Image 1 (cartoon, rainbow, N blue to C red):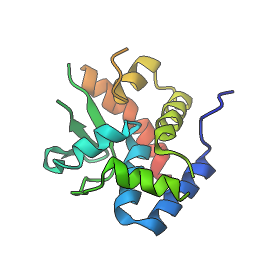
Image 2 (cartoon, rainbow, N blue to C red):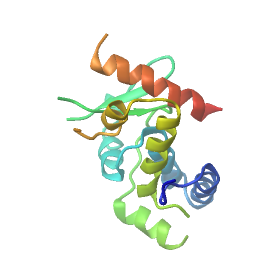
Image 3 (cartoon, one colour):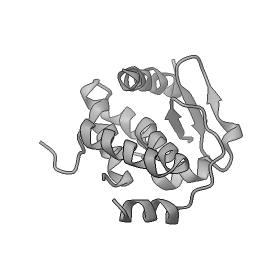
Image 4 (cartoon, helix red, strand yellow):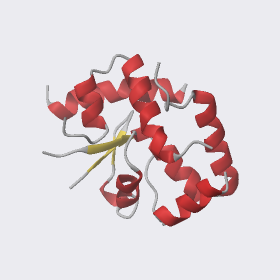
Length: 145
């Protein structure tokens, strides 16, 4: 009951298409799928990947209250520009900007409260970060399977 939310299959396909095209581009879509965070925040983060923190289950990157880019696979230094992603899309797939709609949607299926989904995804609308990480862990589990 929501139009622009991709399906797992369409996402699965875009990932593969990106993997065949480039390892750098594939890595960006991968993080987009793990985080639910804007493309711009992803690129800002991959230029300083040494600030990434990885726990046993999930990883997280502190931005700048404060937001975190939650993800699963450790960051490596990637130099893609918005331009090179845009190029990729033009040749094909799901637009990366719709990846966060999917992510927010699965998180809601996994019973993550909307205020927490907003926090995970970077929008302003025990501790705060602790609860968010435990919630994020549900999406991380689902994602690996």
